[PDB]
Image (tube, coloured by chain):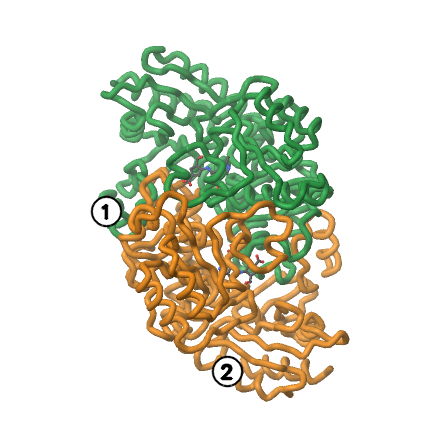
Chain colours: A green, B orange
Amino acid sequence: PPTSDDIFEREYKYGAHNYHPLPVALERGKGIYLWDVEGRKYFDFLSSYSAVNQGHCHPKIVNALKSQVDKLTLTSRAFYNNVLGEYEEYITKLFNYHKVLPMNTGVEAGETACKLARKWGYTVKGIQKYKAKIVFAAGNFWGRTLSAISSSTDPTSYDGFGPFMPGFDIIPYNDLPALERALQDPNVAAFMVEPIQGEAGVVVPDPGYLMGVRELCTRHQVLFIADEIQTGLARTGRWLAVDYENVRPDIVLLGKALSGGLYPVSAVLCDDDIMLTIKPGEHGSTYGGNPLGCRVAIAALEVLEEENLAENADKLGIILRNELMKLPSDVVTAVRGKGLLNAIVIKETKDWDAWKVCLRLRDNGLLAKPTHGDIIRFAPPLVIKEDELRESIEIINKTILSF
Amino acid sequence: PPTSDDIFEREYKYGAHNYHPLPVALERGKGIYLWDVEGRKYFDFLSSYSAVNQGHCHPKIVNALKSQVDKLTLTSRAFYNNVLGEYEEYITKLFNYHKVLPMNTGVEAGETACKLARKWGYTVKGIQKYKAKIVFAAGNFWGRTLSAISSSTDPTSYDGFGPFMPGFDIIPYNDLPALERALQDPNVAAFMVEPIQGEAGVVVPDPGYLMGVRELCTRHQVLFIADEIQTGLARTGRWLAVDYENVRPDIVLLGKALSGGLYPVSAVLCDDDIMLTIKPGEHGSTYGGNPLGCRVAIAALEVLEEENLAENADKLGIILRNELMKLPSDVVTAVRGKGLLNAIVIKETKDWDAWKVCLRLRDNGLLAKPTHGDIIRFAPPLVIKEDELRESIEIINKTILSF
Ligand SMILES: Cc1[nH+]cc(COP(=O)(O)O)c(C[NH2+][C@H]2C[C@@H](C(=O)[O-])C[C@H]2C=O)c1[O-]
Ligand SMILES: Cc1[nH+]cc(COP(=O)(O)O)c(C[NH2+][C@H]2C[C@@H](C(=O)[O-])C[C@H]2C=O)c1[O-]
């Protein structure tokens, strides 16, 4: 029966050192709760960066996976499977776009959007071959490929990682005058932006930012790519975070909770005039659109809809933020978020930091992760109930006030 | 009860047109066989580009997936799960490298290898920041990211897809004098190469090519990255295709059959002096190393070992190629491959092509895919038996000789 310490040391030996995780070794998860190898129980306040919006191992999603794995799991796209088309019709009708392109990981959805933007740039907009530019916001995080780190302003992402992808320009987040300036160049094909920046520390832009982005993109014939990989699927209290301002992006990226954490599924949504710039043989993925992922994804979306999780995230979010704001201003300097995507900023000294807070939260039965040594994310599954939420808030209060 | 035609038309409407698949709509798979929605039974001679080496829905691998999905599926790498370390110890000991870095898709494993090569280049070799070059072989295929298409010589991969990643140089495959010439530049960090090129049409290099590559890489202080995503895990009749020449690459990429097609799992293997150039916070993936994928991967490897599939692939491969060589030289111009990774080249006219052959193979109960209009791949699951193989060969003979 391996201990928590055994688990840590074994990984140190045989695995890459590309992470420094919070020292907790989990073996079971159900709904809002996680259990470690010692049998200790925890509130999950990370939800695997929104991948388990439905709670850990939601029985509807598990039943879909169990049913389909006995039938067929992977043919490759060399042939048709019977599930993919059913999934495609369902998701396209739900989000109201003509088409979906299926992939596996969030970064793959991002790479696909970049490819679409360029191909649309050259074939429709009329940009001269390989002059196409994509604009990004500072603080952006969309993954770990050579392309994705090329748009990052985080030195931990890019430093040491070889020459960078050309054609990627960076402007400040939440800055309409900067976007307006950037879009004067007719060689800009697109702007990719997160409606709230997750990894940057739940950076919520000013009211009107999303409608301003939509207006500028349309005016200058530029694609608006919304990365809703973390913000989508009910986490902020709507189907999409862009719904708060009734904004329709050209391209929508989804991932994470698209499978309830059971399978790496991601999706790129857009209309025919953009989607069909990519011809047969010009893009894909071995596992993209496989029948098992598709069955899981259908069930995952059905859960979000059936259980009205968006409404729940909105209602409980307000409660969470209001209670967090009662913590002393000397210790917690800001509270931010929408729905159940939230964070606090702590008054870090050399004595005390976000890591130390998260260690004590763990000791008191709640799992959260810091994102810069002063930021702590609070993001439980959307299936959490009010009494469960208030019990969690009591843990958070006990912990913060115990210093 | 949707028909095959319904399935095709539904995808045409709601899905991207990034594929033109063989018109067959599958709903069930078990071992070597696939069933379409009409109930027709087929030999799978593609094996999802080697992802289902173990056969479709292998019960040992399915049982691992079913057992673990009830426990825990995804925590993210913000915390530890109990499975990952067990998987890491197992795979590292099996292939005899210090460490593994887990990812999901084949292209992600490739991106990771490129990142390692660059970081090792700058930090160990002493290359000036962002002068690091990676060399690739013409005909290479490692995925569909902006980086991956940047090394491709296939216009269908790269054309229309925006400016390219700098620092990627291309030489002819199976060409030691060319490698020797390329490696004169001290800014080369690595050479990435497939031991047999899969997507290029099962291009088998000359005997001694792999040992020559190893010798040149060592001499010029350059990393040898072997992409065994398709060739690895028993498909060619050894654990790794590089085993045929007793060659130890610096970095080994694995994917596909690493999960038996049940889950997108991929792996990057290397020793500490390379692996540890990447520090905590500098690389990762949401789903990489999740407990469900790990349980599946352990079971998938155990199958390959337990059932001696490598030995089986070697024995049956010889039989397959010898029988294929009996087809008239006027109609089939070449037979090539190792183990159960094989292909034929047909004497394409304007009357007749690889697509037409694969349509008739399907009609006669065997599923294969063409790769250039003159090349047809023959790659059944490694669990196939001799009598099953000979029955398949009879289908292939009937089809070819029916024109
Ligand atoms: C908005 C958005 N867009 C694309 C992606 C790429 O998604 P993916 O990882 O599936 O490629 C992500 C993933 N965010 C992660 C990755 C992670 C790790 O441990 O690697 C830390 C974490 C916190 O933000 C994302 O938030
Ligand atoms: C040696 C090697 N190295 C890396 C990868 C990337 O793997 P991945 O797709 O998981 O990113 C592959 C995948 N080969 C595929 C992809 C495919 C599709 O339909 O996309 C057609 C097919 C035929 O070769 C590979 O053979």
The chain identifier of the residue carrying mark 1 reads: A
Q: Nearer the viewer, residue A369 or B103?
A: B103
Question: Which amino acid type corresponds to the residue marked 1 in the rendered image?
Answer: Glu
Q: Residues within 10 Å of mark 2 (few under 14, many from 20)?
A: some
Q: Which dot marks residue B386?
A: 2
Mark closer to the observer (1, 2): 1
Residue A79 point in image, percent of width and height: 64, 62
Is A258 left, or right, of B253 in this rendering? Answer: right
Q: Is residue B74 above or below residue B44?
A: above
Say whether mark 2 and mark 1 are on the same chain: no
* Residue B215 placement: quadrant: bottom left
Residue B126 point in image, percent of width and height: 31, 48
Q: Which dot marks residue A9?
A: 1
The chain identifier of the residue carrying mark 2 reads: B
- For image coordinates 58% across by 83% down, the residue present is B324
Residue B158 point in image, percent of width and height: 60, 53
- For image coordinates 40% across by 53% down, the residue present is B113
Is A214 left, or right, of B82 in this rendering? Answer: right
- For image coordinates 48% across by 46% down, the residue present is A262
Q: Residue furthest right?
A: B351
Q: Nearer the viewer, residue B397 or A171?
A: A171
Residue B305 point in image, percent of width and height: 36, 69
Q: Nearer the viewer, residue B203 or A101?
A: B203
| Disc 1 to disc 2: CB gap under 8 Å | no
Q: Is residue B51 above or below residue B351?
A: above
Q: CA distance from mark 1 to mark 2?
A: 46 Å
Q: Is residue B387 above or below residue B70?
A: below
* Residue A68 placement: quadrant: bottom right
Q: Is mark 1 within 8 Å of ligand 1?
A: no
